[PDB]
Image (cartoon, rainbow, N blue to C red; front, side, top):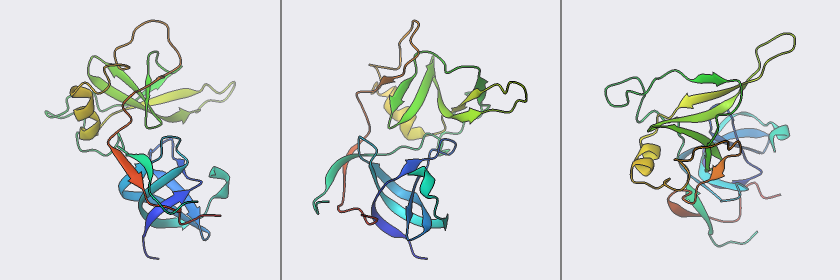
Length: 186
């Protein structure tokens, strides 16, 4: 099938790849190209590509609505374990979420002296009980690091103390707009 450039509603973000997805006409679509999301995550604008059968369980006007250009922190433009990005390439399995993490575009980040890691889902590989691990993968996105370095996360990336809940970054990305209505409007 051919790609659909436009907005979808009833979208979700995969917790392992951090890519956005939506169902339309019984097909599963993956958001590619430049991805723009609404602050409340209800809608995503992108170059939607048919990637498989629809999965319903994961789930207007005509003028553009406010949103933000999404940065996938795992896009590999600044790969760890290199001269460029010396950070350790190996993701950790935390018994619990690290303290002092912050929310940026629905993704949860940890900053350890300049090395950024991001929450990439749980991993329950046990038996009795089970043991649930929270995987934190090293950020491989140059865009994410350019924002951090320009101090765009000064308000949330340098906290210390016993703080379990993530703080929400004031900066939510490059401002943009999503065309309306969503293509998969009910």
